[PDB]
Image 1 (cartoon, helix red, strand yellow):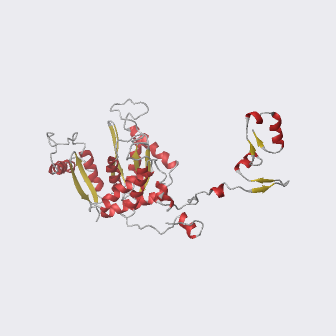
Image 2 (cartoon, chains in turn green, brown, blue, yellow; image 1 turned 90 degrees about the vertical axis):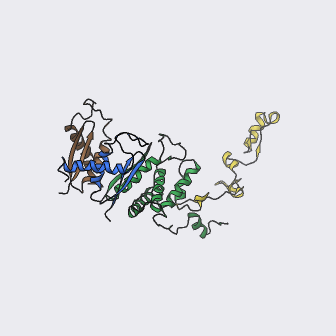
Image 3 (cartoon, chains in turn green, blue, yellow, red; image 1 turned 30 degrees about the vertical axis):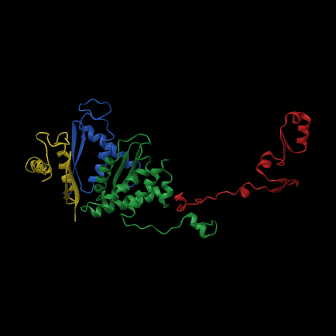
Length: 153
Length: 77
Length: 77
Length: 76
């Protein structure tokens, strides 16, 4: 319906987004000064403290926005929130697939630091849109409470 | 009435368009990824397999759109 | 209410604006071809016949628009 | 690490092996009712997990090797 294509480009990796028409320029602003946050793009996957994959494009973006939601600019209060909720949706949608951020972050660039980077970026937009964690237990604690595993602390 | 100016720019040639307000961003999208379809603009009229005039700006654009109408994307029918 | 953030950027100086939603793209157009009116930005305050501060960003912009109001384009009165 | 306490999906939990379990000796019988000790070795080879190792002087002659093989055992 009210839809406006948005791209996230860096080196070899880009992402496709579908914004409400109203919210398309609020998300253009972030996308813009956010690609300035990024350094000189490598067409490889090695620049340290910079995106390796497309799961990091969204992760690094989600946090970029949540910083300006919670902090500073009061001119764009409702617009930040909408921009957030959409990215958090597109994320839990494609990238997370209804699984935890950790097990999904655990599958990115071999660089240990970056995998943590994805996780803090999510719980940054998770809290900045007020979304509480939903009460799931893990496959571990299921089979734990079902006496397949015998967990100790 | 419901009107929104749209430009088509390449090198020395550009075109002026008047869109309904509703349809102005659907035509902005095509205009955008279409000027990426175009190579590095010459300020002359010679780059082979690329626009010489403004009749070609519209021509090359009309086909760029009709490809995504008939084929692929069903989100924006 | 009906509000859309607009920025005016040149070198070290930028300005923040709050447009009605309807009027946000009309002011985007001016902002755009107006930053083309400006030369290659100095990160200092000395380029002659070009903005030193943010009071000049608005001043130079106000006149840029008033030229297209009074003169020429009747499509966007 | 951390992600294994929160992993949602199936077969997300792994169990550290037991050597007694994983690699424990066993017994099995055939359709023609032989009985083998069930080890990785015997199963691999297809014969009892007791084996006469290669030994130059004594394990060279083609007799003793063929004989020890006719006895259904692994020799080198």
